[PDB]
Image 1: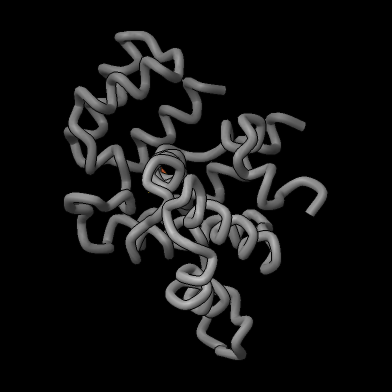
Image 2: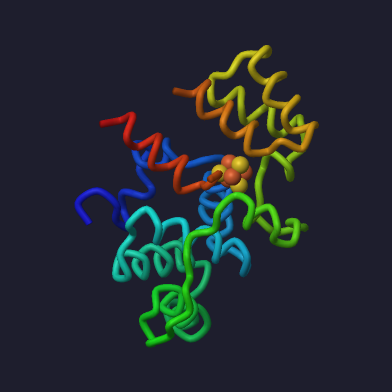
Length: 183
Ligand code: SF4
């Protein structure tokens, strides 16, 4: 828990290593104090894969869902705690829940209104992507290249370009490669 824990996953240092899909899920969680089912699964299993423990996950999800008075702890415990415990096998299930790779993410139903799961290189408009990439200090030529990959449907190449420009396809590999470059 020394490095990855319920508090450090909200730090700029750790979160600077997240790929765009995880950044988007964390932003939706931060703003709405909730994620719908597919996003809960994508984000909770990514965090499990980076080493967020069972206890630290339950802290993280209970604090994020009850933040700013969004729901009572009693409602969280009645309507969500089981689901997050299940993702960690804490009620005894033996389903093999592994972190989702990019192909798996892309193959989930596309996000609609109110959804934050998916792959932003496919799911965001070019304008929204451009604004986000400018926030990450990319220049116009860089953004044009990333958008070229997006328009060709080469979403994991677009994501690889963003990794290279800001420093098998799998969000957890993006995180691990990025985190290693901080050490
Ligand atoms: S390419 Fe994969 S890691 Fe990158 S944003 Fe899309 S789903 Fe996430």
